Amino acid sequence: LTVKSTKQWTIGTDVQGSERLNGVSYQEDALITYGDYQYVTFYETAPAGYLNHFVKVGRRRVSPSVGDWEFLTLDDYTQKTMDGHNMISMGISGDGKIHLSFDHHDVPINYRISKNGIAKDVPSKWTSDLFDPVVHELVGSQGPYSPLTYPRFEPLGNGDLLLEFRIGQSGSGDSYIHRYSASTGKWQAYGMYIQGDDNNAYINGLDYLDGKLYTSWTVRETPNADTNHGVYFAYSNDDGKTWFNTADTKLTKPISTSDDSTLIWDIPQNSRMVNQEGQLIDTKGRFHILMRDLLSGEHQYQHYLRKADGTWTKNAINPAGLNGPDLYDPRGKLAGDASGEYLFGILPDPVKQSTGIYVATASKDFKDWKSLAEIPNTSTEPLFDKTRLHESGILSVFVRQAGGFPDRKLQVWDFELDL
Ligand code: NA
């Protein structure tokens, strides 16, 4: 596997503040290809200036040829909270509607949707009046909608879309799932799916494939990030309603954090393992987790693999040149190609201030981590476009630069792979 071409686009000037609001690990998702177009969402500074931001949505054609990015500005909702949790997630349902949820730390939901199926019936002009107003509920469903943190969308096989989030707080919280029907345009409540016990679960993502939904998490005892422990796994065959552990034993609904039957790796507190890193169901149905720890005596990224035979392995990701991360350094992701043979680590390097792209192969049990490419000058938790990789073999990554405001840009990097 090699790189055929590298291209980049600047899509905006990043916002100013003590926190990163753009390029946050648990954006799910920031960058999406649907049909022949790619979409991206981010904050830009509003005319009021410092500590006033608007959500922007960009689109560009990517098939059968790539055209120019265009942007709309949602100038009816001003983001004002300088808190690194207050990021944006986007999802696109099979009716072509684009959904956004954003700007939360332990507050009520903020959600909006496009009026029509703009990703399906693609409009000529790209303007803010394509979107309905911000609301604080999910029409058809029920709360609780507060205190909410961490909206995450997952598109299902039939065009429906899940929205998942935590209700409660760091160190005492539960998570919930809601399902949007692309046939009726109504949401329904799947209810609480994981319940804290004077702690909270921190999932790594949602991963849906061929009718199964996969998640992994660590449990956090207090608002101190040193109090994460364990790596846990469960999956569902019914889009979030009921769940199983790795041995296919049905769990209680909700899953409790006190239930050790979902633990796949013991990792104590003070291991320097961070919450909400990365996960991946590969196209062959092998599940992967990206985390980190200091348990070897050095800080290293860690790859957990759920093998076809049922067994779990844990391998450090330690290719030449990669500096290992500590607890508060930027988080990475794992991406997969269409074939399921190639695993990409998209790993921010805290020494280099860059994003490395490393590749391993299923033929070598993913032990053969090799440097494939680099994105220079990043201070970001890198995020990629699953569908674009599957469909065209192009690894497209959304990044916040390193550097000072207003030099620090937002960009999209495309690596064309020679599959
Ligand atoms: Na607690």
Image (spheres, rainbow, N blue to C red):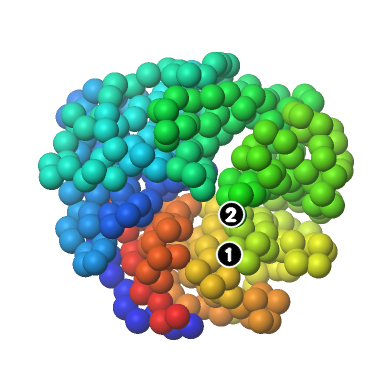
Mark 1 or mark 2, which has the lower sequence index? 2
Q: Amino acid at mark 1?
A: Thr
For the point 36% across and 39% down, which residue is it? 95
State which quadrant residue 370 falls in. bottom right
Which disc, if any, is residue 297? Answer: none
Q: Secondary structure at mark 1?
A: loop
Instruction: In the rendered view, tell whether residue 92 sits above or below residue 80.
Output: below
Report the Cα–Cα distance between label 1 and label 2: 7 Å
Task: Tell me where residue 367 appears, x and y as whole percent.
Answer: 68, 77
Nearer to the camera, 193 or 266: 193
Looking at the figure, which quarter contains the C terminus? Answer: bottom left
Q: Amino acid at mark 2?
A: Leu
For the point 24% across and 23% down, which residue is it? 76
Instruction: In the rendered view, tell whether residue 67 sits above or below residue 178.
Output: below
* Residues marked 1 and 2 touching at CB (< 8 Å): yes
- Assess disc 2: are there few (<14), some (14-19) or many (≥20) residues with their C-alpha within 10 Å of its C-alpha: some
Residue 257: tell me if it is visible.
yes
Task: Tell me where residue 255 appears, x and y as whole percent.
Answer: 77, 33
Residue 221: tell me if it is visible.
no
Nearer to the camera, 83 or 364: 364
Nearer to the camera, 139 or 263: 139
Which disc, if any, is residue 283? Answer: 1
Residue under label 2, please give it.
209
For the point 56% across and 33% down, which residue is it? 164
State which quadrant residue 50 falls in. top left
Instruction: In the rendered view, tell whether residue 359 sits above or below residue 191.
Output: below
Q: Secondary structure at mark 2?
A: strand
For the point 23% across and 57% down, which residue is it? 61
Task: Tell me where residue 49 appears, x and y as whole percent.
Answer: 22, 30
Which residue appears farthest toward the front when viewing the image? 183
Task: Tell me where residue 191 appears, x and y as whole percent.
Answer: 64, 24
